[PDB]
Image 1 (cartoon, rainbow, N blue to C red):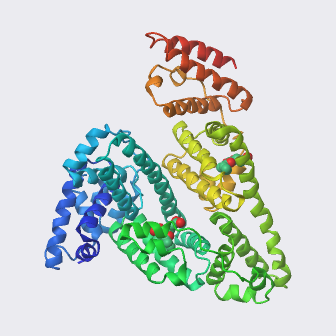
Image 2 (cartoon, helix red, strand yellow; image 1 turned 30 degrees about the vertical axis):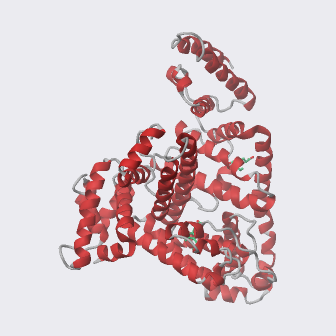
Image 3 (cartoon, protein in one colour; image 1 turned 180 degrees about the vertical axis):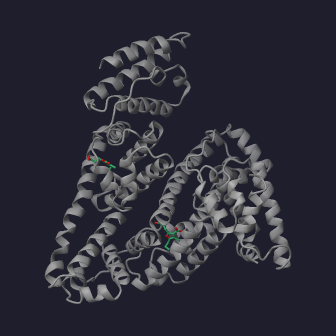
Length: 569
Ligand SMILES: CCCc1oc(CCC(=O)O)c(C(=O)O)c1C
Ligand SMILES: CCCc1oc(CCC(=O)O)c(C(=O)O)c1C
């Protein structure tokens, strides 16, 4: 029995949680009650299996069972069988489910609901997160849940909870979104590009983090990590969590052979141990390391070694280059590796290979400078404009690049891209590139998966599917879509009401940014000069109307003077 297997390994508490997440992720629209129902029914069945490992259908695979249990509450998907049936669900996951925004009751109600029923208050948290983020890294969701519990458990018995809980909950919402985004990139890499693409990413990333580890060690770590994510991304949450535990054990047992910063991590609870290991900083770089040119460009055996085991050889190149460049972003290292490979492919087919591939490092110089100049520029701009204005600048840029993309996606993607400014610019040159460019890769992947749902721009498609590692350079190279036909104004789109006054300070900027997008789509060829001079107007329209006697009509009146002056510029 497979269910029995995993149950013992995970226990009843984790087993129940993971199954709840699996269900909320497949059928995101179904109510909490129903999932809870199916979870218990499934959990009890598991209990009978532990005992009689041949009872009902304890012989079956998790998918069969899980699928049949969901099919008692959903249709075409359920008509199919085994493989096809499961693939069906995976394809129907919704990255942008039409779910009501989630509002949180006053501190008092929460603590009551938490204290009264603790298991229920937590199961609902997992449910509400899993259904909105169909790809959240399961094992990590269990880690946030405990952290969530610790928040209430501590803050509800204090002097002023509002002050103690609200903050800690915000820190959790944000970090939970970042995590969700990082994991969405991992699944997309695996699902749209193949495991080879993910392995390459892992080697480079783990080699930067574990500089002292041996190639054969990193390779072992990479092979295992790949399996973990291959399972979590395919919906095999139980085995994923299981496998992820093993990997954490291994790493801790063999610390000395991997990194010296793993100590603090291995001295804590499972869930906290895994999370800690995944986020540990880079170990110090080994002292006396030879020059890369030695074994990779000067040696005359290059082509022979490349021919013998193209995969191991390139893998070794990446590890060697990555380990000594924690200052480079993972995508840049992958671009370098791609450049080196392309060179051996053509060069090793020449008369004198050596001569041909002798200057490959001169091919790197341009690739290393592009990212550095981009970062240097944009951080200088960020420092001058501040976050809000920087996001506006990016908003104008991206809309002009890909005007067809829906206004909600553009606004979300641009705001996020703009956060790269606060998140990375404060770091010194040395750590800026990994921070900025790898973060940009997560954000642009967001754009790509949201866009794939309803394609409207061949330019977004091409840049999203051509190369995983070149996405950022592809997007940056775009300027203005010259074939784009300007949109025609819509009264409703630019009519500001008094309801924007109740909305939070941020919910306002968001509205103004939404208006800026619509503007740009209407006047692509407009300049940043006019745009600014118009934005400041909208600001005025809010302050007036919002504080001017009983006026819900000012919105139509003040809005009239607005559009009038807006149609003029
Ligand atoms: C095996 C090395 C430690 C490690 O690293 C990662 C990826 C973190 C990242 O993406 O940078 C994980 C994980 O995904 O669970 C673990 C465990
Ligand atoms: C901090 C980096 C974020 C960033 O900055 C730019 C402006 C580049 C330029 O000045 O051309 C882009 C982009 O064009 O896509 C991105 C992404």
